[PDB]
Length: 154
Ligand SMILES: [Ca+2]
Ligand SMILES: [Ca+2]
Image (tube, rainbow, N blue to C red; front, side, top):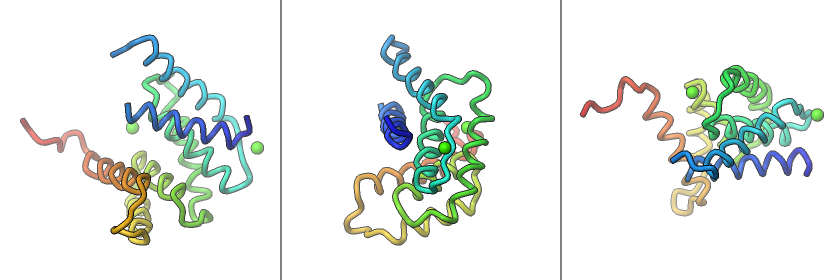
């Protein structure tokens, strides 16, 4: 039940929720992701890898849950600020790719997309992992859906 265990659990649950109408279970799962995000939000870590995993869990958690108490947008900016403070120190990894992609989705900071495409270029097109394929798809969807007013007219 460590900070890291909690963060990895939240990353997994937030992913589960996003890759899945208002049933008791649907509400329970959305509520649990909010509850877990709220519990972890006040935690601070000096270790950059632990801090990266905490931030990624929180950004994923608050984006996954339908619930918003009116303070979620403010809390996401606190998390983004924590990510910008460690991004340059993180080594190339799946974690760093996920933080760049989720951070870009919240900011549309072209420097984050640029760095995310450079990380992609380091992988093997002939043998991408299941997670690499998924995060590439997620990044492309954020890039294509920046502006709702640009949606194809039909
Ligand atoms: Ca701490
Ligand atoms: Ca948003």
